[PDB]
Amino acid sequence: KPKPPAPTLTVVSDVATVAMEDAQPATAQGVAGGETSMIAPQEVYAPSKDTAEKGEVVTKAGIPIAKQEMSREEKLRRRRREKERIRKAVQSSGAYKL
Amino acid sequence: WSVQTGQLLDRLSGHEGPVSSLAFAPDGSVLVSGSWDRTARIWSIFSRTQTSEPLQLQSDVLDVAFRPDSKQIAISTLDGQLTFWSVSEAQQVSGVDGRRDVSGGRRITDRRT
Amino acid sequence: MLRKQARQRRDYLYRRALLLRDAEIAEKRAKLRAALASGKPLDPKIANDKELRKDFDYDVSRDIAKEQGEIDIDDEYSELSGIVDPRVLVTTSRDPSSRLMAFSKEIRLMFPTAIRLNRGNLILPDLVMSAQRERLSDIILLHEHRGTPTAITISHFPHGPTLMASLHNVVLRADIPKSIKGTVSESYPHLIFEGFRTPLGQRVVKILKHLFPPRDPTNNAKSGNRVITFVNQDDCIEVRHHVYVRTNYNSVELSEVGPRFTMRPFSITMGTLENKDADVEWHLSQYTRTGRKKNYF
Amino acid sequence: SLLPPDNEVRRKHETLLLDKLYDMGILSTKAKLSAVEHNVTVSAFARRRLPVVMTRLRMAETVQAATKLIEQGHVRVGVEEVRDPAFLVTRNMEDFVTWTVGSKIKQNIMKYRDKLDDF
RNA sequence: GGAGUAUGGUCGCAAGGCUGAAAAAUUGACGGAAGGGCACCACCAGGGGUGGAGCCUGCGCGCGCGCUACACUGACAGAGCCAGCGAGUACUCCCUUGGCCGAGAGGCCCGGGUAAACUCUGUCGUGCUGAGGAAUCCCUAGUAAGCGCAAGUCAUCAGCUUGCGUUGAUUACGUCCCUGCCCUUUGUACACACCGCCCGUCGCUACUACCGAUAGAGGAAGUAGGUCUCCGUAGGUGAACCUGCGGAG
RNA sequence: UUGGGCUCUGUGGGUGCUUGGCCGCUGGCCAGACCUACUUCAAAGCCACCGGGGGUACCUACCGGUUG
């Protein structure tokens, strides 16, 4: 039996494939290859609550929408969906007789 | 396992011993495993109601491979024989020996011919 | 394969006898550690035991984790507990009747990842070898007298126990008409054990408890509307299985749905189903003198 | 042993060594550092060489027959053959030892139990 | 005498009736619509019980679970041919007329009450000599039914139960449309890829203001950029040398 | 086919792609032969495999000292 499965990270860079590669004079890759940066657009930026601006909030679609422009209807609906996410996770005689 | 979820889909089973060889059908539907259960197991998976099927062997399994024309599947068994089976009619279209046809030996440290 | 199961069987027995000897020794070992902890004097023999001191300094800490409850003791069971959703099959004796096959159906529906098989004219050691060939985790033979159930055999593979137990006071589903009863609610229920206090008691508790899918450990109390209840008085394991609805936090409304068993267990053979070379771990001992009166469990 | 007893990584190394040796084939328990302390044995490694494990598993009679047999090569291990009589055999493999593709030792067995079928 | 380990005796506390049976909560409560998976407690195809007569255990005269009768699936006669469980000095169907030998308790003797199946060949030809409705319930590969032969496993089971061998099929083996059940709309690992903020009624928490009795608890509602070298200098620890300043290459 | 067989031993080849036997070799020899000269200058370090826990009276080594 091999080992205990240990948690382990490996920090990538943003370089190209042919930059990550080993030592050759000229890659097997052509010209359409040789430019992708090892990290997707999701990696280079994720729209999220912690990176949002002040007056606005982002959706699950990834759309920053303003609390100011938002009406009470979708306000309550958004709060309802987030709550559902959480859910799935001696005195006086005058005072007495009167 | 499933490449999008990454969590364990399923244990399959039906094997007297370890599964020595693995091959998939290029259509996307049929699996074959081959093992020292003396079994060749065709695994009917991606319909709803999964099943097995045995091809019983006179011998034990060392490797399996496919035809891209996915009706045909072949088995290498350690007695040497190779066998082509029709995959739907799970039946032997042919078999042949290979012992003398690969008998090249006298490795050092052996007192055999 | 059959080789490697059989070799693991005998290996497990060998480790058990070793555990007996080392447990008798460790009875003398455990006396040291707390005596070190409290500074109180000990018996001077156990003091002047040389190998005890050397082996002590090597092997305190497993006893520490035993005290902590950290570690998982050796048995048939505790290899893969909360990992494999334990597959359970059921099959009656050689030629079942109608009510019997319906009650086996129901008890397939009571244990929730249970598949049912029908047995036909099929041979008992080959059923055992075939279940072993599908890598199960249970098998349950349930016998009949005259359109009523008799005896459940909760056997647990790869080489654990067969609890053969007579049932008493059983009445089924399929008498109550389909309008009054409903189709069963198949969810991963909870499990509640009432009154087990002897080590044999908790042994039987273990072999019942691993017939159930591992409830997801996040909100075990709130979710789930299905519970199953084993409870014993006069050694008599009695089960009632209830779907509740919870009208308040001061009142919960039950619904009796699973059947009514009161099983008395008469053997735990530490050997699987057919294996008549059995290691009799316990039995209902009638026929002796005060074995009628006194209580196991 | 030198490590203090309350150390989590100490218990992890304990269970580590004992699990790897219990699946190796040297030891007998999985619980005692003492058993590691004066149970681990060059005779235990010797007892896990492939001659003596086919003796105990009752292939041959004693380790002469076993060792000569392996020299002229009659014992497959799962799929490979065997030339080199110190192939250590773990507890997992002590079941899948068996005889080779067709040898006269296999036919000694089968000629005796009268299942000799030349096919 | 020290240390434990018990066994029961002794004493203190627990052992003083504003009493008289029938919540928490920012997380909470219940739903609905879309999306998948599953199921002989679903569809589709089929089979087969029970339910008709009787026997009868069990459950409360009723009831099902078994067993048996019911005619072409015929009989009778011959011939031919194959199994698995199976071994404790151990297993018996009764109860009686006579007689024997027993001075008596008995024992004798005679009466009365290593399959099933299959296959083949001939002899006869339907004949009180009629295969179970509504209902329901079960079942998908050695699965259903039919057949026997054995064993009797402390518990239950001879009114049977359990094994094991034999002959071995149709019909599905798709589908979530019915009934459903489960679960997605949170969390749970990132790629090329796709999608694109379900909905409801309320509750609870913060705030706003109101109402009126006699500061007040309530009722109700709403918002959350000059280096190198040379020179001329001044000072420094002086030949030199260093520093600062000013000119040249 | 005017005798033949088993079995063992012995020899040579081949079981790998065909460029000499020897020597103090740009040369000589296989019958050989010649035999003891000549001389400017020791060295740069490092590495170096003993089964584990344990003791160190004496020896070895290292380090740090001490008289001469």
Image (cartoon, coloured by chain):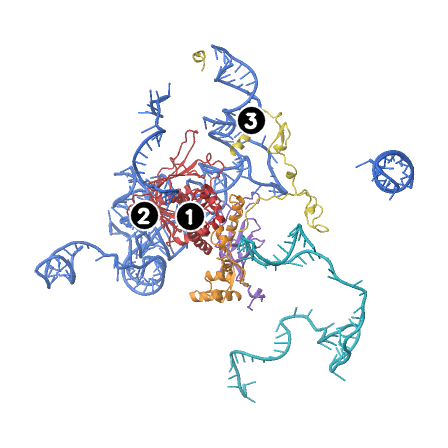
Chain colours: A yellow, B purple, C red, D orange, E blue, F cyan
Amino acid residing under circle 2: Ser
Q: Which chain does tag 1 point to?
A: C
- Crowding at label 3, few (<14), some or many (≥20) Cα neighbours within 10 Å? few
Amino acid residing under circle 1: Pro
Amino acid residing under circle 3: Leu
In what element is the residue under mark 2?
loop
Tell me how far mark 2 sits from mark 3, CA to CA: 68 Å
Residue C28 horizontal/vertical position (percent): 42, 48
The residue carrying mark 3 is: A76
Q: Is residue E185 above or below residue B79?
A: above
Q: Which chain does tag 2 point to?
A: C
Tell me how far mark 1 sits from mark 3, CA to CA: 76 Å
Residue A95 horizontal/vertical position (percent): 45, 13
The mark nearer the N terminus, 1 or 2, is 1
Relative side of C265 to D15, left or right: left
In what element is the residue under mark 1?
helix
Look at discs 2 and 3 and give the one toward the viewer: 2
**Viewer-side residue, C123 vs E105:** E105
Q: Which mark is residue A96?
A: none
Q: Which mark is residue C285?
A: 2
Q: Is residue B46 above or below residue E31?
A: below
Residue C41 horizontal/vertical position (percent): 43, 44
The residue carrying mark 1 is: C44
- Crowding at label 2, few (<14), some or many (≥20) Cα neighbours within 10 Å? few
